[PDB]
Image 1 (tube, rainbow over the protein chains, first blue to last red):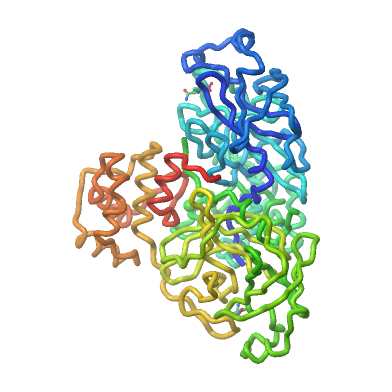
Image 2: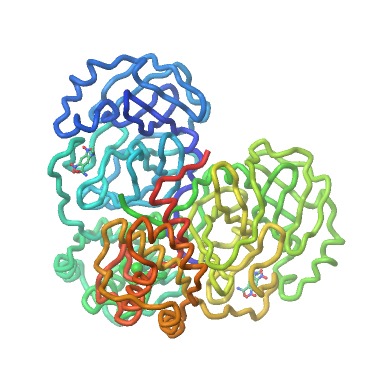
Length: 306
Length: 306
Ligand SMILES: NC(=O)c1cc(N2CC2)c([N+](=O)[O-])cc1[N+](=O)[O-]
Ligand SMILES: NC(=O)c1cc(N2CC2)c([N+](=O)[O-])cc1[N+](=O)[O-]
Ligand SMILES: [Cl-]
Ligand SMILES: [Cl-]
C-alpha cells in the first residue's frame, strides 16, 4: 500500500488565504470569520527590522492603511489590533469559506501541514514538524510570511503555525495563531541561533512500525532493551529521551504488529549504532522523524476529512 | 529559504471527488462538468478480478446500478460508457466546482500530485513521479482506487493519473484520464511484475541545482565530464541516459547558478562512485529524483495558482 509524507488536503485553508499590504510591504493573511490574521512585521520597512518598536510604528497606521485583498476583491478594514506578534484586522465581511476551525499551540515533535503562499495565492503544500529546538524545516521565500500550518480532524482545521522568518542557517521560525513565537525567537534582525536539532525518537519508532506494516522488515532483530538502556543510546545520538508516555502512545501500533515497543527500540538502537549499511527504509537512507504515531495509524487506516 | 517535496494545493481537486458504488464495490470518482470518471473495476466482485470480461459484466449494469454520491448528495446517472479502463458516468448536474482543467498523459520522469481519497473523501496529498518503469510509488489502501494525480498551472488543473491497483511488490499502477494504463499493466489479478526502476537523472541534477541554490554545496568539485562519459556511469548505476534535451532543460538553472551542466554531471558522477560518505543533501541521504527542473525553478521562485 506504501507510506509517504502526506499533507492534509488544503482546500479548506486555501479559501482563507488573503494578501495584506501595508505601505510598501506585502505578505499573507488568514481570513477566518471577520478577522484577518497576519504577522505584525507587515508594518515594517526593511530598515525597520533591525530594531523595530512595533507599538510606535503602529501608531502611524490607521485601518485604511492596511490593504487586504481576497483573490480579486478588496476587503474593508474596520479595526485593527496587535496581539503579541500578530495583527488582527477586523473586516466588514465574514469569510464565506471559513471552515470549522480552532487555534492550537502544538508541542515539539507534533507534525502539521503548511500551505506556502505568496501575495495571498497558494503555491504548494507539505508536511512539517515542530522541531525540539522550535524551528521548522520548510520552504519559504520572501513574501511567504503569513503562510500557515495546520492539522485537520474530520471537518475542523486546527491552525497551529504562522510563518514569520528565516534564520541565517536556513530554518524557519514563526508563531501560533495567538502571535506567540514557538521557541525563543523574535521578529527582528538580530543574532538568533537555533539550539540542537534533536531527533524525535517516538516518531522514528512510529515510522519503523509503519515500515514493518509495509514490508520493510530487514531491521528487525533478535534483541530487546529497556527504556533506561535505550535512552543511554539516544543521548549519544542527540535523540529525544523516550518516556513511558511515548511507549504508551505506540501501544496501538505495538498491538497491531505484534512487536513490543521495547523490541522496536532495540532495532532502532542497532540502527543508530551500526547505521543502515547502504540499505533503505520506506525509501529513505536515514531515520525519519516527522511522522507521529497518530500519523502512522491515520495513514495506515485511511482516515478522511469532510 | 529551504526546499521540500511539495504538492500542489489540492482544493480545486477536492471539489471534484465523489464516491461511486456498484453493487458491493465502492471506490472514488472524479466529477468534472457532468461526467464522473472512475475505474472500470467498480463493476467487479473480488472473484471477478482474476480474469474479468468487463464488457460482459457491464451488460448486466444499468444507469441506476451506479450510485454516485458527492459529499452528502446523490447524483442522478443518466448514461454510462466504458472508455479503455475507465467508466464515464454521465450525471444530470454539472459540478459547480469544476475548475478549468485538461487531461494529459504524462511522460516518465514527470511529477504530479496525488490526492488520496477513500469513499469520495480526501485524506491527504503528496507528490509522485511517473517512474521509468511506469509505476508510481504512492500510498494507497483498499478503497483508494479512483484517486487522481494532477498538476496545476495557474488556474488550470491537468489531470494525469487515476489509481487502479497495487502490484505484489507494493508499487502502484493506474491510467491516464482516458483510461489507458501507464506502462504494460492490466486491471486484473495476474502476474504483473514491474521492470527496472531506473533513476531519473535529469531530476537528480535539477535537485543538485536546488541544493546549491539552498546552500548545500559540499558535493561540488573541481571536475567536469562529457555526456558520453557521464552516461557510461549512469548505465552502471541504472540511471536514465542523459541527453542534450535534458542538458537544455537544465539551462535556466545552469544560468542562474553559474554552474555548467556538465560540471554538475561531474559532481553527480562522483556521488554515484563514492557515495555520500554519511553526509546529506537537502536533508536526504540518497539522491532525490522526484523533482523536475520545472519543479525546482517553480519552487525556487514562488510561482502561485489562482
Ligand atoms: N535571516 C535573518 O537574518 C533574519 C531575517 C528576518 N527578516 C525580517 C527580515 C528576521 N525577522 O523577520 O525578524 C529575523 C532574522 N534573524 O536572523 O533574526
Ligand atoms: N496485488 C495484486 O495481486 C493485484 C491486485 C489487483 N486488485 C484487484 C485486486 C489487481 N487489479 O486491480 O487488477 C491486480 C493485481 N496484480 O498483481 O496484477
Ligand atoms: Cl516528502
Ligand atoms: Cl534519505
